[PDB]
Length: 103
Length: 103
Ligand SMILES: Nc1ncnc2c1ncn2[C@H]1C[C@H](O)[C@@H](COP(=O)(O)O)O1
Ligand SMILES: Nc1ncnc2c1ncn2[C@H]1C[C@H](O)[C@@H](COP(=O)(O)O)O1
Image (cartoon, rainbow over all chains, first blue to last red; front, top):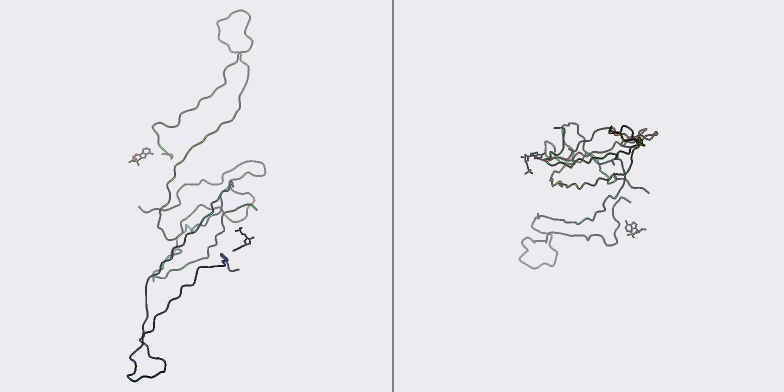
């Protein structure tokens, strides 16, 4: 009901964590659990490649259909673009429904 | 300079006319040319099939390009459509230049 594709077997969950690295243990055995860990984090790269199937417009409609277009008028910032401070921004939500079909 | 494709061998000219049909000649030979013809016209059907080759957009442009779109707002008549009296009309000229490329 928010939108999209209901799936019984959706793309799986990818889980990740940093393996614990203990700090120096005591020199006499104690069965208590370690609260002492080396503070660390990890970084890396992630790629996602999805293959989307398309359904083409077959319409016989004579007159021009609405399309999603960028405003031609000048502006301080360009839409869907970084600003002077490097911050990416999306000015408006874009739905997918423009082309028209008959019932 | 008006536009389009300069051609040294452009599509040929297709010529058509109605073959003359004389009216009743005199019964005594006269070498004068006939000014007397049966008034007639012809109608028919004509088909033109042209095969146009296309050059696709390869652009890496991030932000959305301008497109030619129909106005969403309501109106008495729809653009590029017949009116109540059956008259087809084109409200505006449409150029071909929307998509953007670099120099
Ligand atoms: N989002 C979504 N996911 C899964 N199943 C759905 C969904 N929406 C509807 N349905 C069900 C009920 C439809 O009549 C049928 C169409 O399946 P068809 O493939 O068109 O034969 O599938
Ligand atoms: N409209 C038109 N018709 C015919 N010849 C033209 C036209 N415009 C330019 N030219 C000539 C001059 C260009 O440098 C060359 C490009 O041919 P190319 O095919 O790109 O190698 O062809």
